[PDB]
Amino acid sequence: KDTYTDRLDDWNGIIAGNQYYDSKNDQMAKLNQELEGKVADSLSSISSQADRIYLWEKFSNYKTSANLTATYRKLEEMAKQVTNPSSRYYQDETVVRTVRDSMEWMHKHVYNSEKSIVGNWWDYEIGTPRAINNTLSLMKEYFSDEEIKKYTDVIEKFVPDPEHFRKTTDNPFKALGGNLVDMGRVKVIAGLLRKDDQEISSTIRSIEQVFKLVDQGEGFYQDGSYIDHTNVAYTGAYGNVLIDGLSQLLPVIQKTKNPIDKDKMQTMYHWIDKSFAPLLVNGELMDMSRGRSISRANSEGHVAAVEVLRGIHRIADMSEGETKQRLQSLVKTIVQSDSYYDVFKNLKTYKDISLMQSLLSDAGVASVPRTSYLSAFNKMDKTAMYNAEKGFGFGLSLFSSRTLNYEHMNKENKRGWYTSDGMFYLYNGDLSHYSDGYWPTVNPYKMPGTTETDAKRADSDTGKVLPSAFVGTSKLDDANATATMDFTNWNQTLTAHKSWFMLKDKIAFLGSNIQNTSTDTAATTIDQRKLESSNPYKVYVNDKEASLTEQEKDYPETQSVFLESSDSKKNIGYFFFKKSSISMSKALQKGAWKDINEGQSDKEVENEFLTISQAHKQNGDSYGYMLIPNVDRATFNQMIKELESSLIENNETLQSVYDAKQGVWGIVKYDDSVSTISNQFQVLKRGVYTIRKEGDEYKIAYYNPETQESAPDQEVFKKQH
């Protein structure tokens, strides 16, 4: 036909890739079989109506916008198979007719220009229009140009401006990040289908906004943070949509008369290296970066990670030289380190499957275990740490006056109340920990690391920002950093100076100034670990075996707790600097995904959890312990003796832990008094510090979380360096 019907061909190769199909290819045949089964179900359950109310009973209530998108996606599945030579539906007369009669019908009484958004705007402007674009693209040899223009003006009615969404509503918003990328998959393809040049250029120019790093608002930040929905850490969900969708569009865009400058797209590599990579541990995308998507059963950590990985892979493929090879190695080593999830379970096109196969089988592409790293995403109040020597990852989830604690919208993530109240994540040998129904079965009132009262919480509640701006991380190097959070709970009845000292192979948890003005009981959850019936833990308290029961058991004067597995890479030890009174229990916890997400299954799920907590019955209370993972019992026992005097201070103004082996100090000052540390030096300013002694020299890493700035050494450190 023309150049539009050239770009659409390339698009078809990206979103379906029928030209790359090979029935002798194991993985490809699997996806093909999945699509065959989907189309069969659709064709057989579709109402062979003399014009009935709906096309599919499962998606009957057209008041629920979700049913529109779900309906059109079914037709896209048909378009993919009708154009797949190896499909039983290849060029099938009934299938070709169904897709047509279905477009006309939906276009008649459901989705048209004379209609208005009912329910979720996303389905009317993004979900449905994408499905329509793809269907018409794949089956453009069966549809009339006029027919194409006809079924597409509705998209022009609801989405006429490439810079704003919800245009037809009484409250539109400027498209940025993920949503803006989807604006391209909506208007760039629709523009190619309607052969609309003004639509193409205008949309491409608008998309370029995505390559700009911001220092406020939504988008990618220089420090790697990614913000969306005004002030929510969202690299792992909306960031995913951004890289996933943009990597699909680029090959087509660069072939149009409106290609994007190579220097503008250079930022993509910054996102990959600074924003995405740090959040991927053993093939899992850290949940603290995925917002409300953690409440979706079909999108657990390892599945979500593939959205990012396939995007990075596509980008590597369009890159060249060392950039291509290095990105290939990144994808390769991450996928190969994931012994739990089969990456192919989330590669939904033949080209993506093909790309991954050649990459994994190419001896020329290096696959070396990733090195240690520590990312302080201060712009979104999250911290990611990874130790390659011992093999564990650590995620610190916070929020401040600058960010929302948790997102609960569209009936999703109803119980994520405390997922950012100083919650921590440990990624060890159990790659399945936060998967297999962790989210619908975890006790939402006892999120690990959080200090809270036992007051009941409402599902209808929504997120909030923190009163204080004193929340941040001071990173010294790839293995050492210090963080703090001037904590106040949701209803201002409890406070706590919570601090963390990341010291290479362990993390110290310090809490002071714990006060409670309510009638509710206060306690800190040391941990709530999901267990594996296959890898049982042998629990030790003060180095003596203890048998945990479903009923809580109190352990006063506890100096240590050790969770012993057959696999040392799953061991977890907790050393209490000062003998503390804790309680522990191991119980089966049941729940359904619907409990935390209305649109999910109400099917019962259950998991066993080991809960450790410390009650705070008095004002001025505190806690202090060292988390030591991936070491055996004897080694753990040896380490706590080494850490005997590691606690320097833990009060209302000063908190500090010292690693004598490393010669590193972690320090948090809540005021500007002169603090003398280990009779060696003095720290003089409110803020966060991570210091290292190398001979008579001192390496200083200072961070003022409120002003988001460091400071000259002489202003904060004494006894220049």
Image (spheres, helix red, strand yellow):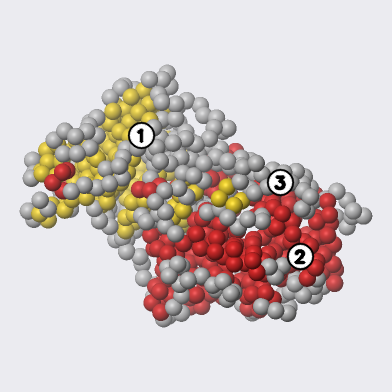
Left or right: residue 154 compared with residue 105: left
Q: At label 3, which amino acid type do we have? A: Ile
Q: Secondary structure at mark 2?
A: helix
Q: Name which residue lies at 62% across and 42% down.
A: 171
Left or right: residue 425 compared with residue 307: left
Residue 187, percent from left and from top? 64, 62
Q: CA distance from mark 1 to mark 2?
A: 53 Å
Instruction: Give the residue number, with chain letter if any, for mark 1.
Output: 468
Identify the mark nearer the N-term, 1 or 3. 3
Instruction: Give the residue number, with chain letter if any, for mark 2.
Output: 149
Instruction: Give the residue number, with chain letter if any, for mark 3.
Output: 117
Left or right: residue 412 compared with residue 611: right
Residue 688, percent from left and from top? 25, 43
Task: State yes or no: discs 1 and 3 in contact (Cβ < 8 Å).
Answer: no
Mark 3, residues whose alpha carbon is within 10 Å: few (<14), some, or many (≥20)?
some
Q: Name which residue lies at 77% across and 48% down.
A: 115
Relative to residue 9, is residue 555 depicted above or below?
Answer: above
The residue mark sitting in front, 1 or 2, is: 2
Q: Is residue 15 visible?
A: yes
The residue mark sitting in front, 3 or 2, is: 2
Viewer-proximal residue among 342 and 499:
499
Q: Is residue 537 visible?
A: no
Mark 2, residues whose alpha carbon is within 10 Å: few (<14), some, or many (≥20)?
some
Residue 572, percent from left and from top? 34, 47
Viewer-proximal residue among 695 and 144:
144
Q: Secondary structure at mark 3?
A: loop
Residue 53, percent from left and from top? 85, 48
Quadrant in which residue 87 is drawn: bottom right
Relative to residue 105, is residue 229 depicted above or below?
Answer: above
Q: Name which residue lies at 66% across and 55% down.
A: 159
Q: Secondary structure at mark 1?
A: loop
Q: At label 1, which amino acid type do we have? A: Ser
